[PDB]
Image: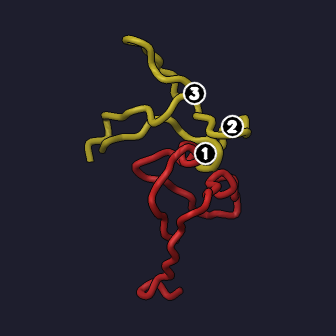
Amino acid sequence: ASVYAWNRKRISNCVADYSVLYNSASFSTFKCYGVSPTKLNDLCFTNVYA
Amino acid sequence: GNYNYLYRLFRKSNLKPFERDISTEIYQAGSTPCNGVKGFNCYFPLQSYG
């Protein structure tokens, strides 16, 4: 989307592989805050949003 | 910022009681033997509070 109206999607009821994302070398930017990207495949949350 | 004060972000093992390690070698986050690679799979370990 045009960023003033940024896309939102609820992520829930599913396992989220972050390893494919931190492995995705085509990302010109890939950054994490409050937590390490390597830790994410151990973590759990009620929801996530894209 | 006063940049003179910095902390190690990550290490392959966490400290034992008063363990000391001043090595600034590029941190390895994945399968890449770093050899000077920074920003993807490998990183500079010290971060300034600035």
Given the image, what chain letter belongs to the residue carrying mark 3?
Answer: B
Q: Residue at x 41, y 40 (%)?
A: B47
The answer to which of A47 and A22 lies nearer the viewer is: A47
Q: Which chain is yellow?
A: B
Task: Tell me the element at label 1.
Answer: loop
Query: Percent position (x, y) of residue A43?
Result: 51, 47
Q: Are marks 2 and 3 in contact (CB under 8 Å)?
A: no
Q: Are marks 1 and 2 in contact (CB under 8 Å)?
A: yes
Give amino acid for label 1: Lys
Q: On the rendered structure, is B40 left or right of A10?
A: right
Q: Which mark is residue B34?
A: 2
Are there few (<14), some (14-19), or many (20+) residues within 10 Å of tag 3? few
Q: Residue at x 45, y 36 (%)?
A: B9
Q: Which mark is residue B8?
A: none
Task: Tell me the element at label 2.
Answer: loop
Q: CA distance from mark 1 to mark 2?
A: 8 Å
The answer to which of B33 and A36 lies nearer the viewer is: A36
Q: Which chain is red?
A: A
Q: Which mark is residue B38?
A: 1
Q: On the rendered structure, is A18 left or right of B17?
A: right
Give amino acid for label 2: Cys
Given the image, what chain letter belongs to the residue carrying mark 1?
Answer: B
Q: Which residue is mark 3?
A: B12
Q: Quadrant of residue A24?
A: bottom right
